[PDB]
Image (spheres, coloured by chain):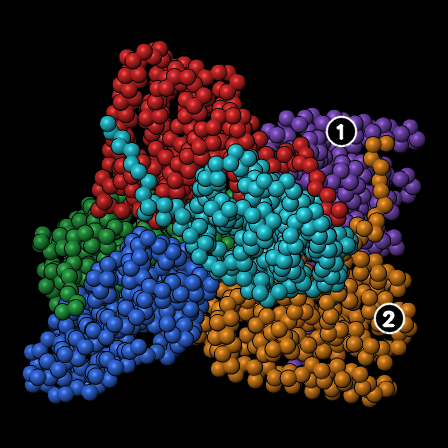
Chain colours: A purple, B orange, C green, D blue, E cyan, F red
Amino acid sequence: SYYQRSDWTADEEQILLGPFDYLESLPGKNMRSQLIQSFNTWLKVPTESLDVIIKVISMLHTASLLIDDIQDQSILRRGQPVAHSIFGTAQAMNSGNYVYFLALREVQKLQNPKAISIYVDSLIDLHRGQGMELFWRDSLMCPTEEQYLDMVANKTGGLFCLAIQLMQAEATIQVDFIPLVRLLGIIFQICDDYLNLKSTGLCEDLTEGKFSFPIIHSIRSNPGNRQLINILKQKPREDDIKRYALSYMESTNSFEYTRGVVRKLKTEAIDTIQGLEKHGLEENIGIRKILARMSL
Amino acid sequence: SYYQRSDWTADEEQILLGPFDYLESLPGKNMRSQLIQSFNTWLKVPTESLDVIIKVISMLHTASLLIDDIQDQSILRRGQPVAHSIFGTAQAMNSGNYVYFLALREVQKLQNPKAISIYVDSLIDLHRGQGMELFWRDSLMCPTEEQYLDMVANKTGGLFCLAIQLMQAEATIQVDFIPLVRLLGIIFQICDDYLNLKSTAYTDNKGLCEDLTEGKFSFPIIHSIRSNPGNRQLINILKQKPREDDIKRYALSYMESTNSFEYTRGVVRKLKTEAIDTIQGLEKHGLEENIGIRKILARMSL
Amino acid sequence: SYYQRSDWTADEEQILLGPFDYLESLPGKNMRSQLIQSFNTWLKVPTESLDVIIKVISMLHTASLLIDDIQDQSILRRGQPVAHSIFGTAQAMNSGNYVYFLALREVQKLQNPKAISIYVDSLIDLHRGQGMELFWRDSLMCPTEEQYLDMVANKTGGLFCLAIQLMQAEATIQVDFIPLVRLLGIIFQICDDYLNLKSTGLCEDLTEGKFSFPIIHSIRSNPGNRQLINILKQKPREDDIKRYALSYMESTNSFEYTRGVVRKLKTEAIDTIQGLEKHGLEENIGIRKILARMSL
Amino acid sequence: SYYQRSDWTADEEQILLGPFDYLESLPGKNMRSQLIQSFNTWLKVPTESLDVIIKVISMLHTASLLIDDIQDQSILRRGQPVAHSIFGTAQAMNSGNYVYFLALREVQKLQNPKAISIYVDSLIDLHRGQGMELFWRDSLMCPTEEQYLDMVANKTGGLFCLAIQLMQAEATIQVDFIPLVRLLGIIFQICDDYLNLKSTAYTDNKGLCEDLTEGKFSFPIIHSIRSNPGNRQLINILKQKPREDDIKRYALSYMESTNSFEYTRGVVRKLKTEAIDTIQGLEKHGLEENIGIRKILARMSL
Amino acid sequence: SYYQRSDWTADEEQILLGPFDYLESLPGKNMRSQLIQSFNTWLKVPTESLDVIIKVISMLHTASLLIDDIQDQSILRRGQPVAHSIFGTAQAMNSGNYVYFLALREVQKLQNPKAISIYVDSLIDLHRGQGMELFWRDSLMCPTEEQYLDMVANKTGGLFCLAIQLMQAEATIQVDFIPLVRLLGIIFQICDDYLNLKSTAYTDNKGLCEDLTEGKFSFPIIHSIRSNPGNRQLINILKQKPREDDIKRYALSYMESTNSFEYTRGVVRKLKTEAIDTIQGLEKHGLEENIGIRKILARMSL
Amino acid sequence: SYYQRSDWTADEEQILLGPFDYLESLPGKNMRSQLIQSFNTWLKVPTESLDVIIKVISMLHTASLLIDDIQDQSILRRGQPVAHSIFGTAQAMNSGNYVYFLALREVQKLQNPKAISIYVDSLIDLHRGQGMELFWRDSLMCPTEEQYLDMVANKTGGLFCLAIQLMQAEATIQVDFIPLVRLLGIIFQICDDYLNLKSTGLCEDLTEGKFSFPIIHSIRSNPGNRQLINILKQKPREDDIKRYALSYMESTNSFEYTRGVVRKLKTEAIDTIQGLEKHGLEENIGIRKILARMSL
């Protein structure tokens, strides 16, 4: 009687989604979507469910950008200012975790008894990946390549795998695509690492102190030289430190090593793609295109 | 194959849970699990289900402390360092949101279909309340008391309501206890606001007037700001996020001049009366007299 | 006997006027002066007094730059470093307030019983304007256009009006020019706001968190979007935040809105100028030129 | 018309005066209005004029505290937060200079033509003294004692001299009291310098040795620096602007080793003797014996 | 000629030595010059040579405090400000390395050719130990206890060993005392590590647990970190370099739970027993019983 | 028995010399070496000793760069990032002071009874010079030209003189070259000061607050203007402050004054060089080349 509970208003949603709406208004390379499209060539998910899945994955992806940019302490995002440099850390963080749960509500629309478990297991894999990455960063402990790949499997596989698993759960065909999906996420992340250092901020991964795939190679290629790992500790904003690091990683042949690893991995994926097709699946051009987009 | 997927190990769980386990080992008031037990006098949920519910609510509560101490830039927690000042904010944040989803997995063990929707709706309300509170905070706009209470109902209420709705989902009695529990969450939050400013117990556990340092528009702060809009001293103090004891001291003195601490006591007094009436009303409809719930209401007092 | 009061020396003046002499040595757009010249076409102030007034207004103008640059936390001034980044905050502040009172001593040379009251009322209007502007800035409270204009009347009218009022007090003609003078100061300030965002630091008003005329328009044009007002709170030094804000203000048509307001205001001034001339005043080319200088 | 000029409102005055009103409500020593009253025994200015003078001098004094606390980067004021740490420096600064001109308007009410020139010359001296003090401060050059006293005569003296010159302008007696009042302002400032370092009353009101934190070349600091130029410890401490109590403590200890606090007492002793002689001299020329002025001199003592 | 070379003056020495002289005037424990005197019972170095040795070792010790307080970012030293917080780091650093070479010049006065090589080898060991300690520090890698003891032998041991090797070079007795003195330097450093955390005497002289603020992997810290690798709380605290007393307090509490302070006492106990055996062994070979050396061993104790 | 002293390993040397090895891997203008070569035309030091001396001087020079960059708070070094911005202050400092003593061990290889005294006296002169320079900087006390030159004699003469003195101590000829060596170091330092402000970071000496030769001239040329010395106090990172200072030093004719001083000093050196040659020394082309390299 003294307290009268009010309904939630459009204006309040608008406030809560400010950081989220901002990010969504920035053009990006929409690739989770193309990945969904080219797996749908095989899975043929009914349209009403595919739209639900696409919206769930868009939401989760954007929400996790809000959070990752805060936790990585990035400065740019699709070339425009990072969401929390407009709205502040707290509202960006909370906006993104809010969207995690709007997405779960959206997922409930599949009215599929397995969809909740699929969502939970992905979000758990997500944070498990991002947690091991923060652990190495904060401890200055360089992982092995193998350790890095298991982490990437979790933390970039998480949403890749989430999308395809939901599609699988809504489709009639019972082929297991997840191993291939996980490969593509690993390739995607390794390419990302490479492009962050070699492509037209300058090497934001160095500023953030991240043990990325080529940085790992360079540090371990000659553990007697501690210049690179010490640069990571400094978390350098300066272009002159970054340019020096870049140059040292050239001397260790680490960009050549990464290119050859991506080559080896694309070859496994094509081989795998051909396996599924030699077993009664339509030839998939769209997925070969996706895999060509990653190349460097 | 080049990639050889591996199993998650206990050593890795331990890393992921470091911040959470740190917080979990500092002693707390356990209001929430005592509130559950008082309601279980009426709802009589079996032990197996009730352990799950208690575990889910305490996972979610610790998790959100992890996150809220970061977003509030708090310094102490249970009179000990905030988790993120040991582990850093990134890992403290990630561990906290990780646990949100460990708790979702945990509530699946009820194999109750209403349970997922209850969980979803409550996490949503949590973030809605927290989101409006940060909005006023960052914009320097003082809410009305009514707006404050709507937000508290979502933020603090959302987790009280989650605990009792899960119990209701696990019980066959068709009484709605949620209004009562929501009322208790408001009373609890207003008491918390008052104590953040007026007690050596909380001033030893979170700092002298940490709500001032954070710039939070709490219940007595709102009252004192709005009771004399021509004086901007208090809201300017909030803008400054003072760590100094002298500013906080002056602000506290100012709020006594506005009779705001008395105003709050009076409000809490009216709400607790409403709470007792509600309890007595439920009991006048077949329920046994509930001493535990009277004792938890009591232990929210000044 | 133990204390012997010493005279004030040229060397000490030189110290006290260091920040002031520095600013005066930087070329600027000298417009208070042209405004005085083109009103003198009508007022014909005797030369000895006009020189006193010109010196008083030069002093006050430069002194208030010393102070405004500190209070706004600017970084550049006429392209060169801001006075307090050479001399420090305290000496720049004190140098400027010192000059306020040297000017009052200079004003006493008019030996006009009204001149002191005119000076006091202007300096009061000055600080009243700058105080409401700090109040909105520090409180994140966006004023209305109407509120902003009353503030500008006070805080840019103050020295405009001061100059013309002294001239009026020293002249024989009794025409009231102040309403027109105040209009011109409002036009001058709105143009300044526009030029601060669209012209060749980049949008120093965003860094300073100022509710300027186009920013006000943009914020209020769509109060459901809080991106701009939140950028103001951040007080951004980064060019990427400023560029984004700039772009958002384009989308709200706020530069088009400001241009049309300045158009409307120039038309009132010409109309007013023509009124005074249709009542026995020389046709004033110089003031029409001044008003053309503001255009955008 | 598009522009519709509006009147200044009381709500707006209140904003403009927030910092000033804040300071004005913290209790002070009221040396200045007591000094005026002692001189009024001799000058016998009518109440109406004397209220104006007292109001002008207290407006100007509060205003310049607002400004000086910013320029000195002070932390406390009358044992309370500095105005700018509630209101921010911009508004605190603007409000302070605003009041300078409210006071100019206020002194116009004497309708005394000498009054404007007196006001102008004193504000000029104020800024000249403050300006030399910042110059030594920022350049790390220690003045001589003589230069220090010239600057104090302008800075602290300028506002004592303003109060008594306005009274002289409102009186027909043709005695010059300004030399005496200037002497009193020096004594007052030297006492202030000593007490900033040597008293729990001022160390509770402005902090432990706040003059050190600010880097001010005060009277005992100058003496101690110059008495042994081969030791640069003290002047290097000034350069550092220490907030830590340990540095300030060490510096205080150093200045005792230089007998600087004794040196100051001795100087203050000589000046107060000169002050009494001057008073007795004025009284030996027709003026009634002035007990009040003897009591204010007394209450400047250690 | 345009350039007219000039002589170095006492005024300039005084500047160069300001930081050094500041430190030199704060009272210390004088362990090192007492250790020299105890060994001189056996080595019986003439007074003239022994004064030189004592002067060289105390120059080098003060110099390296100057430098180590900067590199460790220490706050207090002998319960007084660190030299560089008066003089700034540049001058404090330069003065300290200056003195390293004044001491080299000073040791030349022995006109002993072994002396230069002894000096060189010890300064080398100093920097080797300090260098490994910063390496672990900055990399966040906890050494093993064995690696810690190797580093301590170089860093703290290097200056004990320097003092006694110079004495050996000035004596004709052909006994090797260096193993014993190195052992004493380890015991001394482990005691220092323990006391940095567990005594109001050292907590009043260097701060509450200043080793935590600095991130140093000291003896009990290493033990406590390594005794439970699954808990990363302590090493994460080191990473944070906490100045707050609450974090340091929690970390201290954590290390008690790991029984690390007991572990250290036990280690120090074993080393002191080894030290006594060594002494007794040397004495069983012609040397007179040495009470002084037993008393300095004693005064390293808890 | 409980403690077992371990030997020092290559891996540990590698750690301790990390900052040092880094610096040595950056190309620099190798001039201490050319100075040694062209004095060896006269001194003809036996090869085995000349190599020892060269290594000692290389070590000391690089080590003192590690330290000076920390104490000056520089940011660049031979165009690449400064050593302590990779390794941190403490390890760079300690790496450099370690090398001081490795060099002393190296010097012992000359097995020359005088070499230790020569080393000590140079290192003392070094720190005496750098100490007076920090004293003026930290006290804002502008030295006289004459004071500055005595300081430079110590702090840039120190290693110049050290090199030639060791060569002298290892050579058979007994000519005293030190006065000429000291002249060349003074010329070298004055040229350095000039080039730091006029040459293609921008005026790092202003950022560091250094009283260099032209800055000294400018400040003292008109002590009534305190703009330059106040810029020094600010230690400006901004290019706009530096550009303004640069311009003010132009107006004081201070770069013209420095060029004329260097002219006067080169003329003394040539005159001195010709003296030594008119007394039985080979004509030295190499040293005239060195002296031409300094020119501006």
Residue sitting at x 40%, y 70%: D206
Could you tell me if residue A56 is visible in this image? no
Label 1 is placed on what type of residue? Val
Q: Would you identify the image quadrant in which residue B131 lies?
A: bottom right
In this view, E7 is above or below B126: above
Report the residue at 90% width, 72% height from top: B47
User: Which residue was labeled with disc 2?
Assistant: B50
| Label 2 residue SS | helix
Q: Amino acid at mark 2?
A: Leu
Q: CA distance from mark 2 to mark 1?
A: 51 Å
Q: Are marks 2 and 1 in contact (CB under 8 Å)?
A: no
In depth, the one of B232 and F140 nearer the eye is F140
Residue B228 percent across, percent down from the top left:
47, 78
Please state the horizontal and vertical placement of residue B136, each as a whole percent of the image.
56, 65
Would residue C119 appear left or right of A120 to someone viewing this image?
left
Label 1: element kind: helix
Residue B7: x percent and y percent?
A: 85, 45
Disc 1: which residue: A261
Q: Which residue does the image show at 19% across and 71% down from the upper left?
A: D182
Viewer-side residue, B188 vs D161: D161
Image quarter of residue F190: top left
Give the image location of residue D112, x and y in percent.
13, 75
Q: Residues within 10 Å of mark 2 (few under 14, many from 20)?
A: many
> Is C66 above or below relative to B251?
above
